[PDB]
Amino acid sequence: MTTTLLAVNGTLMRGLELNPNMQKAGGIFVREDRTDAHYRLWSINDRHPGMIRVNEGGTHVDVEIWQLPLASFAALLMSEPAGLAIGKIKLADGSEVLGVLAENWLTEGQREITELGSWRKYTGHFH
Amino acid sequence: TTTLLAVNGTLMRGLELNPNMQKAGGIFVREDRTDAHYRLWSINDRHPGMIRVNEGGTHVDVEIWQLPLASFAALLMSEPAGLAIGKIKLADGSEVLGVLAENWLTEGQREITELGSWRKYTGHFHT
C-alpha cells in the first residue's frame, strides 16, 4: 500500500522472462522511459543486461518504470540474477528514481552494448 | 516479515543513522565481516562505500541487521545516491544483502581498504 518506483532495463520488463516475478511482487507498469546519458550497458552472458553509471561515456538506456509495494523490494532483489543491485538512477528528464544496476565485477569478460542503448534492441525481444 | 542486511557505516550501533534504523524496526543480529573480496572507501569522510573485486580486496567489518520488509525499501529511498543494495558474501561463505557503492561514487575518494573498518577509520567504537 505504500509504494515507490523502480526502473528496470532487462528481464523484469513486460513480457520478458523474469516479468512474472515483477507481477507477483505487486508491480504495476507505469511507463516506458530512458536514463540520462550517463550509463554504460553490458550483456551478461546474453541472458540479461547490466548497467553502470559513469561520468564520461555512457548513453541513454531504455527502461520501464514500475510501481512496487515497499514490502516487495527485498524479495524481488533476492530473486534477481547475480551481480545486480538496486540504487538511485537519473532519468533523461532529470528526475531520480530507484533502478537496477550492475556491480563492476559482473561486467568483466562481457560484451558492452552501450552503442545500442537497449536490451530489447540487442536481443530483438520487442513488445 | 523481515530480511537481513549487512551494513558497514553510519547505520551501525551508536552511529548517526542508527536511531532511525532502530525506530524502523531494525534489530541488531551480530557483528560479522565480508569475504576477502571487498575494497572500501571513505566518501567525503561522511560514510563508507565498498565494492566487490576479484583481486585486491580484503575483509570489511559489518553489522548484520534484521529489518521489516518495508523498512528495507525505506533505506533504498533514503541512502545517498551512489549507495546501492546488492548481494554480498560473508567470511563464512554465506550470502546476505548488503550496502555497496557504485564505482562513480569512489572516484577521487580515499581508499581505506587496508584498515577494513569504518570504525577504525573514524575512531568511533562500541564496547
Image (cartoon, coloured by chain):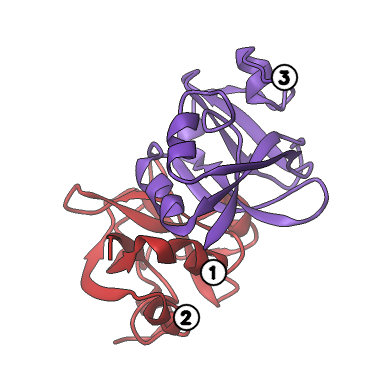
Chain colours: A red, B purple
Say which residue appears at 47% left-offset and 23% top-offset. Answer: B16
Amino acid at the residue labelled 1:
Glu
Query: Is B46 rendered above or below residue B72?
Result: above
The number of numbered badges drawn on the structure is 3
Q: Secondary structure at mark 3?
A: loop
Q: Outermost residue toward the right?
A: B92
- What chain letter is assigned to the residue under label 1? A
Residue located beneath label 1 in the image: A80
- In the displayed structure, does residue A45 sit left or right of residue B24? right
Residue located beneath label 2 in the image: A18
Asked if residue A116 can be seen in this view, the reply is: yes
Say which residue appears at 50% left-offset and 26% top-offset. Answer: B47
Residues under labels 2 and 3: Cα distance?
45 Å
Residue located beneath label 3 in the image: B127
- What chain letter is assigned to the residue under label 2? A
Q: Quadrant of residue B127?
A: top right
Amino acid at the residue labelled 2:
Leu
Amino acid at the residue labelled 3:
Thr
Using the rendered image, report if marks 3 and 1 lie on a common chain.
no
Say which residue appears at 41% left-offset and 56% top-offset. Answer: B70
In percent of width and height, residue A80 lies at 54, 69
- What chain letter is assigned to the residue under label 3? B
In percent of width and height, residue B64 lies at 65, 43
Q: Outermost residue toward the top?
A: B123
Q: Earlier in the sequence, mark 2 or mark 1?
A: 2
In percent of width and height, residue A12 lies at 42, 75
| In-front residue for pair B20/B93 | B20
Q: Residues within 10 Å of mark 1 (few under 14, many from 20)?
A: some
Residues under labels 2 and 1: Cα distance?
8 Å
Residues under labels 3 and 1: Cα distance?
37 Å
Q: Secondary structure at mark 2?
A: loop
